[PDB]
Image (cartoon, rainbow, N blue to C red):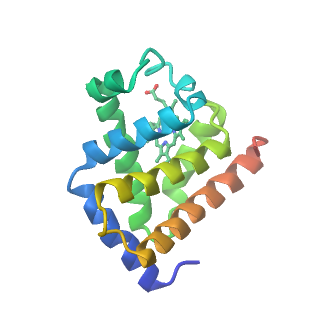
Amino acid sequence: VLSEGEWQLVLHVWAKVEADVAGHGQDILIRLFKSHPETLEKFDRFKHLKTEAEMKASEDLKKHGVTVLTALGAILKKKGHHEAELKPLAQSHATKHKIPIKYLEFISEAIIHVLHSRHPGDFGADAQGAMNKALELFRKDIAAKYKELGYQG
Ligand code: HEM
């Protein structure tokens, strides 16, 4: 579990994101899509985007970026007490969008990357440790619900 000190680091770093949610959200999704092009294909909504230039110009991608990060931010602020918030996300991502848990690992990596890129020398080793733990907890609890539903993998 996370200690209170680690949760404080996580939420202090999250304050950087909240200064510019749409910007961080677009940066994270583009990193995901370019690093792991198979993820783009899970989005009928964005499949048409071929180049990074097109992704950067898409206002709808920014809009989904706010939706995604708004949901993740509310979950982090629960400090692990997130059962009610996680349940619908697990259910829709497992049974409707058909997202393997591996992709949740990829986007976790993309978040860490983007934070380093946007905040050089301002994302501490302690904070990276804490964020990593918090995203692992998120994956673990979603994975538990995937396994229930027969989607483990
Ligand atoms: C930090 C992890 C993530 C969060 C917080 C998140 C959150 C959300 C939210 C709030 C929605 C809208 C409501 C819903 O459909 O449940 C959504 C939709 C969706 N998500 Fe995610 N998501 C995450 C990861 C991913 C990943 C890794 C993929 C695929 C590679 C993915 C694929 C999709 C798709 C395809 C939709 C539907 C978009 C549309 O057609 O409007 N999500 N997500």
Frontmost residue, 45 versus 151 = 45
Frontmost residue, 65 versus 122 = 122
- Which residue is drawn at the image coordinates 44% and 59% (left, top)? 75
- Which residue is drawn at the image coordinates 31% and 69% (left, top)? 121
Left of 143 or right of it: where is 46?
left
From what the image shows, is residue 66 above or below residue 42?
A: below
Frontmost residue, 117 versus 137 = 117
Q: Where's residue 100, x and y in %? A: 67, 39
Q: Quadrant of the N terminus?
A: bottom right
- Which residue is drawn at the image coordinates 60% and 28% (left, top)? 38
Q: Where's residue 114, x and y in %? A: 39, 51
Residue occupying the far left of the picture: 19
Q: Where's residue 73, x and y in %? A: 37, 57
From what the image shows, is residue 36 above or below residue 133?
A: above
Quadrant in the picture for residue 37: top right
Left of 100 or right of it: where is 110?
left
Total number of numbered labels? 0
- Which residue is drawn at the image coordinates 66% and 45% (left, top)? 102
Q: Quadrant of the C terminus?
A: top right
Residue occupying the far top of the picture: 48
